[PDB]
Every structure is written in C-alpha cells, then in structure tokens.
Image (cartoon, grey):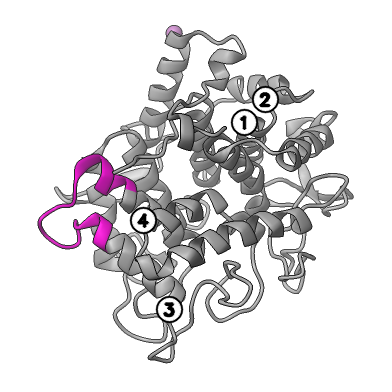
Amino acid sequence: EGAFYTREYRNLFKEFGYSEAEIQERVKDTWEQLFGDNPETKIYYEVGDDLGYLLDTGNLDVRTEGMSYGMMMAVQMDRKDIFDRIWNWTMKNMYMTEGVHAGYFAWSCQPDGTKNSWGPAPDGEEYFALALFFASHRWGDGDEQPFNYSEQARKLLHTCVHNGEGGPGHPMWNRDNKLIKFIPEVEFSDPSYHLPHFYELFSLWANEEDRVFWKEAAEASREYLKIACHPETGLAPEYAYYDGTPNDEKGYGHFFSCSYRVAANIGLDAEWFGGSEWSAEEINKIQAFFADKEPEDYRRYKIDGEPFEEKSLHPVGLIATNAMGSLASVDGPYAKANVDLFWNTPVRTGNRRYYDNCLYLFAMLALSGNFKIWFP
Ligand code: NI
C-alpha cells in the first residue's frame, strides 16, 4: 500500500544500506548545488527581492517545465521564499491573457521575461497545479493574488479540462479518451507527461465538477503507459499516438530525453499509490536493458533497443530516472545497482546540466523518502 494511505515514505537509500546522516547531507547538498551560489551546477537564479527563475541551460531560455519543477522542488523543501519568487515570475511573464491559449502559460521565455512562443506545454501546467495544491496545504493560501494557491490550482485545472467550451481555445486533455495531449491543438500524446498519481490527487482537490474526470484520467493514463512502453525493453517513445505507437514525424519516436521521465513517474506512482506487478516488471525491463551498458556509451535508442550513433544528451538524467524507477521494484534484480550508480554520479556541470539536474534532485528527494504528498 502506497504512502497516500500509510503516510510513511520509503527511504530506499537507507533500505539499501546508506546511512541516515549521509543521505541527509546528500539531499541538502543536491539542493544547494542547484539553488545556492554554486555557479557551475546552479539552475536557479534570483532576480530582485521578489522574482526568480530556473534556466534551461541547453537553450538559454526559461521553460514552464523548469519553473513548475522548481516550484515542486521548493514546496518539497519547505522553501516558500523560493516558491513565491518562481511563481511570481511565472505569473508576470509566462501567464497568457491574450490569444488562443489565454489561461495557459507560454512554454518558453527569455531570461528577461519576453515570450518566445504563445503555445503552452501541458507537463508544466500539471506540475504547477500540484505544486500550488501542495503550497496551499503546507503554508495556507496567501491573502493576495496570485498567492491564493489553491484557487490558482483549481482555476488552472478548470481551463485544462474545459477550455474551448465558450471560446476558440482547446483543452489539454482529450475529453473522450481522458488522455493528456502533447499540446492543446494536437491529438497525440507524450508518455512522460502521464502522471496518474497527480490525477488521483486532482480527483480529491480540483473543482468538484471535475473530480470524476480526474479519477478517469488517472485510470486512462495507467492503461496508456502499458501500451506505450515497449514490451521487451520497457522503453517509451518521446511522442506517441493515442494508440500507444510512436510518433516519429519530427524525430520524437525514440527513447531519448523526454522518455527518461517515464521510469521516474512509475517509481513515484508506486511509492504514493502502491506497487503493481506491471510497474515492477516494467522497471525490471528498463533496468535489464541498461544493465550491460556503460553510461559513457548511452545512446538514443529505438524503443525496441536498436542503438543510434547519437549519444544521450542527458545521461545523468537517465541514471537518476532509472534509479528513481527502483521505487516500483525495490526487490528487482538491478534495483540496488541502479541506486548505487546514481549515488556515485555527481550533479552535472556545463551547458546541458539543467535537465539532468532537475531529474537528479527529484530522484534524490524520492529515493530518500522526501518527495511527499502534502495534505490539507
Ligand atoms: Ni558526510
């Protein structure tokens, strides 16, 4: 039974023999390397007294993926100061009041706040919503907008479900199949965006009129991951059609950066809502696939396992997510090896560090029993 029921979170590092003191130190150090004055590793930058952002170092932009991640990280770490700086920047610079995506958040901005696009990215929205619910539950709603956290979360999720009913907009979930979309104006998906464990919580906390819908989305997503992951290797493509097969129209049909999050998501869902045979077997498959592969040699792979020449752009992120996946298969043949590999991998430096380092801190939090559900 998951932590949602027991309110106890597995410390897999401790279970695998790491000392409580060293785990405590490693979690804090990871946070400090990302959010402190450590220029080589840092991904969070403060602006003035009331703003801050996470920089996508690989593209020199600020993304809703990173901002929503940063808010989730901040609430897990009980850092309301950092949470509010990020959310303030997000509302000021990313929230759209105009155009077909009004009510969503521009997916990419320049560090100066300028929007690079008026299109949103659904995985940002869903993390914003849950981070905001957690903020409300830990700290209470603030007296002034936009710090009225729970109202902001419910409003945002309303738009995600109902957009287009009285306007030219589009929802972020397909209403018939209850699957999250890659972007509001398409009818395909992205396996890594599927967060059934988040939807379970939305089914408790969203507007009441949408709570059954969120239960249905959770179930739809669980079923969808079964058909999206390759049956032998466990690898999921970056984009996939609703029928579960890869969408490679623009090169996203393979196992690469986006896909890495699937193992992590499966890990977290197992920890929160309970183990399943499917999830354990799926994590066993991915870990078995990587068991005989050197991190320095990790590639892009077709989902059936065929290697490309191209190396993984984010191999530290791949390590972190595979290790986090161990939460879904704690007795798995490679579970300990994956956790140990991660323990022995430093936080990344250099221009591609943002994505790896986000996945890294999530894995550090989850594997130490510090990626929690914050209840009212
Ligand atoms: Ni120490």
| Residue holding disc 2 | 330
- Mark 2 touching mark 1, by CB under 8 A? yes
Magenta span covers which residues? 134-151
Q: Is mark 4 within 8 Å of ligand 1?
A: no
| Residue holding disc 1 | 327
How far apart marks 4 and 1 lie (CA) works out to 25 Å
Give the x, y percent position of residue 83.
27, 46
Q: Is mark 3 within 8 Å of ligand 1?
A: no
- Mark 4 touching mark 2, by CB under 8 A? no
- Which of the two discs, 4 and 3, labels the residue nearer the N terminus? 3
- Which of the two discs, 4 and 2, labels the residue nearer the N terminus? 4
Three-letter code for the amino acid on which mark 1 is drawn:
Leu
| Residue holding disc 3 | 162
Residue 153 sits in which quadrant? Answer: bottom left
**Mark 4, mark 2: which one is toward the viewer?**
4
Seen in the picture, residue 29 relative to 255 is either above or below; the reply is above
How far apart marks 2 and 3 lie (CA) works out to 39 Å
**Mark 4, mark 3: which one is toward the viewer?**
4
What mark, if any, has residue 205 been given in the picture?
Answer: 4
Give the x, y percent position of residue 334.
76, 24
Three-letter code for the amino acid on which mark 3 is drawn:
His
How far apart marks 4 and 3 lie (CA) works out to 16 Å
Q: Is residue 200 left or right of residue 339?
A: left
Q: Is residue 136 magenta?
A: yes
